[PDB]
Length: 313
Ligand SMILES: C[C@H](N)C(=O)c1nnc(C(C)(C)C)o1
Image 1 (cartoon, rainbow, N blue to C red):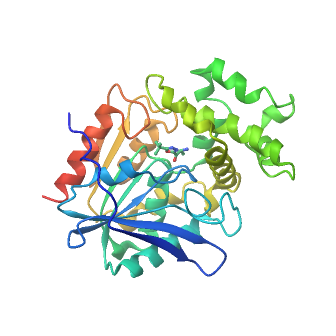
Image 2 (cartoon, rainbow, N blue to C red):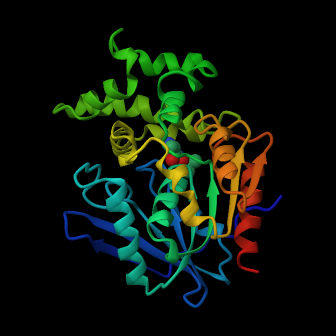
């Protein structure tokens, strides 16, 4: 199976002041004369890591990677002010103009596929092609599956830990219950909930268990991760309608796209990828058997590498 390209340092980076209170971190990697691509991380609030640079051929791609508002190296850390889907779409444009890119390929997995779709449907003429993984459209059925009743039935022993700090009444709406704790004035209260919320996802994003899931418990990461994720879900991704993203697919059906989704993705059900493909015939769908949610699941990674190399030659 195809794997990641070897490690490489970025060739340029900085912070872009948005003008409304945020300084967003960005970096350029690969070849400054290559094909332009933008990497959109997941979460929301997940951040980028050096490994994400290795997803593109260093010779053929010019990759712009950035940390979305409030997470990673973007300041202020864990800020929920002016932190919405539409501000992020605006930020992607600012980064575009700054890199002198007229049009580029959008690569996004999980929440990244969500923002990728929102961005593409808002600025169609700015997207040459798309590589989507672990489709997440933010419909209420998708939120309910992962945070109220669904994935919980496959990991009952883990779900029990997420509910441990909740009273019986709070358990009827876990998202809202965590929203209260993640936004209290007591930072110790916030952190206790942030850890539980983050680790739930870290341990259910891969087919088999991995020690690496523990990194989802680190204070700084967990705090921003939990707050931002919960903030966006509390507001239904700031969408006008439940199915806005699937409903506006007509605006981007002309754009070449590949969809990779693991059969046993417990964070985002394959149904989302099926529904998207149902509305987007032109798109190329790949349901990977034996794989979970994460991008580095062997079978999923293999398809992502083929997809980026293909759009490059
Ligand atoms: C919705 C989901 N929490 C998400 O976007 C996400 N978190 N981590 C990831 C990956 C798979 C990219 C590590 O995706």
